[PDB]
Image: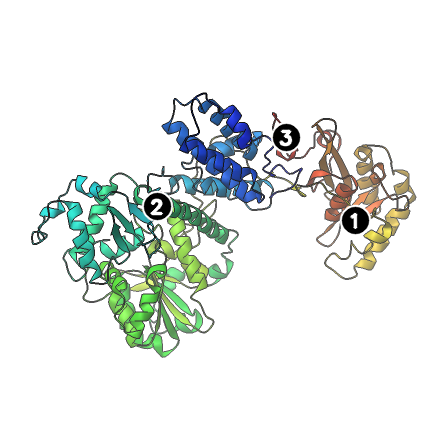
Amino acid sequence: LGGSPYSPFRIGLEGVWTPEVLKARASVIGKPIGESYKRILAKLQRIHNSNILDERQGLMHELMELIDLYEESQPSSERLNAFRELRTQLEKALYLPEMEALKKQILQIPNKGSGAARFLLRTAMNEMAGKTSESTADLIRFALQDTVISAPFRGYAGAIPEAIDFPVKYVIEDISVFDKIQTNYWELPAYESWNEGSNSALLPGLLRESQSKGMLSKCRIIENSLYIGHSYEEMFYSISPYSNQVGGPYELYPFTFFSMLQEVQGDLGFEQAFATRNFFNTLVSDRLSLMENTMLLTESFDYTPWDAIYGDINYDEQFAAMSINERIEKCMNTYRGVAFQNSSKSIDFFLNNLTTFIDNGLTEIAISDLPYDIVQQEISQFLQGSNEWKTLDAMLFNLDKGDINGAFRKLLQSAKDNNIKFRAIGHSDNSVPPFNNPYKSLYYKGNIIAEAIEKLDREGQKFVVFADSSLLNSTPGTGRPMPGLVQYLKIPATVVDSDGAWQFLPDVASSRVPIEVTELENWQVLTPPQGKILGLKQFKLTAGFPTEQSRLPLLENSVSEDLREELMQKIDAIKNDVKMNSLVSMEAGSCDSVSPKVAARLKDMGLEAGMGASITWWRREGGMEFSHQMHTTASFKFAGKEFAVDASHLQFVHDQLDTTILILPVDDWALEIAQRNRAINPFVEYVSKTGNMLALFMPPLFTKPRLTRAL
């Protein structure tokens, strides 16, 4: 997690100067505290006043950026030697010595205070703690290629006027920038009617004309600055994806607006160049949240139930006779759903036999080429028939490259006229091409599949889905396949060729692959590969020392009923076996020769040999020193669960009354040993260890409690 105060992730401050100490250290004769220094001191103050660990580390990443920016832009400052030490302090407080490679990967990302580094450390610590599945490395790969996350922020860092009554995403601080682009829109037919001599003089007219049409309503110019409430992807898909050209009916004006923005943007990222810091930061952390959600979704997905229906190698030729009407009805009645490639033909196909479709079942048509987060409301408004869907209209046009008819518009229309529920399942964020990168692809796909799994879905509804070929079947994913929308919905993927035949789309085993990764510089696997950290704290007894009565209920418990009776007899034979009691020891580290003798004597009494177990831990010594202690036990096996026979436990502090040979399940044994020994950061491997392998057995080095080195 973690806290505290033996945890390596306590994010302590003992090694980070206080503002008071900075002022003495950053002192330069003659020169007063300037604005840059002030913001740094303020931020440091918040760091020392931060009690929630996740916020503190986030803030420390924020301070690092401030120091970066100061270094970058005020490089001859005498305040620098001090600020550099401060940065190293902040680094040493978040990243442990054995976190070196993880650090380089994370702090490589521009904008340490954007929230990426915050999110990624949290992920890394949770992973190292074994408190989560492997994710950090891949999330870092996502971060590094994302067009927002990895972009040095060059957007808008100033204020938003109160007069603005919409949440702002992008700002062009100075309208004059529009007058420095290649194209001269103030010269194109037909802006001739307008009597203007620059692109910035066009701007006010462009907005007025658009907003009288119901478009660009969230754009506003105040005092030489432009404020945009429309999402980059909302503008792209509704203004030119492409296009329209001409004209007509969704006009030249918004297309001129958006083209001008794209010219101003130039070689930069749209958000990189235009975004408010606030919006940039929110985007960064949303993308990481959502990506992680998509990864968790892929984890341990079972292809059995889908393969048991549509997997059969022969299904390709079984699709089909068979007989269109005997199919379709097989999709409605039995499969409850079927997916179509997002092609005019598939729409035109599905439109044709719509009579048979609705005649049993059909309740819902869902497409992915409309973003639900932007037009969901407008679609219901279309269903109501209220023409207040200027945006939805724009996008349908662009989708159909120009309609008449159809095909997407006609599909939506036929949902209205035939009383079938229509729902968008696309998500606009990061939906803009190119899709040259598989993580950019995974993100997009995951969010669509999130909405499909969620707001489909009944349980009372028989559905048809129209989606891109890349979304339907498995794609490359994070260390494992990303299963297509079809697999998640337990339905078949289908296509329609140029001739007009409609058949199943095979999900080839070549699609079911991990992404070709390239190991990150020096990467250390974060979770320790065998065994687990029992907890990043110092373990203590809850009450008194464990007695025979205390442990009595704790074994069963377990999962099964008696059985219990068959256990106690085994236990009592072990406790009362004379040879078993002659091998019991009370010496420190006697377990080394006791366990093998235990395991041997277990075998003779016909008991089934267990893996055994070992627990190792840190114990405070002098100064800030810590030693490692360890203990091992022979064990015996039972229905699914493993039971420990520890004839050497008495070497540790004990109740004077409890038995000589300690018998519990492995996990309970581990906990009890740590507790009696007041173990600090215990590590458990479910295998007995002897001699050599037992000696050098210690917790993972990072779990070793530390200060920093300069207090």
Image position, residue 574 (x, y; %): 86, 47
Q: CA distance from mark 3 to mark 1?
A: 36 Å
Circle 2 or circle 3, nearest the eye: 2
| Side of 512 relative to 404 (left or right) | right
| 538 sits left or right of 282 in the view | right
- Foreground label between 3 and 1: 3
Q: Secondary structure at mark 1?
A: strand
Looking at the rendered image, the quarter that the C terminus falls into is top right
Residue 159: image tag: 2
Label 2–label 1 contact, CB within 8 A = no
Query: What residue is pinned by disc 1?
Result: 664
Q: Position of residue 248 (x, y in %)?
A: 15, 60
Is residue 133 at all visible to an observer of this figure?
A: yes
Dot 2, crowdedness within 10 Å: few (<14), some or many (≥20)? few
Q: How many marks?
A: 3
Q: Which residue is mark 3?
A: 707
Question: Measured from the top left, where is residue 178 in percent x and y?
Answer: 20, 43
Q: Residues within 10 Å of mark 3 (few under 14, many from 20)?
A: some
Mark 2 touches mark 3? (CB < 8 Å) = no
Q: Which image quadrant for residue 353? A: bottom left
Q: Quadrant of residue 70?
A: top left
Q: Residue at x 49, y 54 (%)?
A: 297
Name the one closer to the observer, 547 or 193. Answer: 193
Asked if residue 208 is positioned above or below residue 416 in the image, the reply reads: above
| Relative to 693, 394 lies left or right | left
Position above or below: 286 against 61: below
How far apart are the alpha carbons under marks 2 and 1?
64 Å
Question: Which residue is farthest bottom?
Answer: 359
Image spot of residue 696 (x, y percent): 70, 29
Give amino acid for label 2: Ala
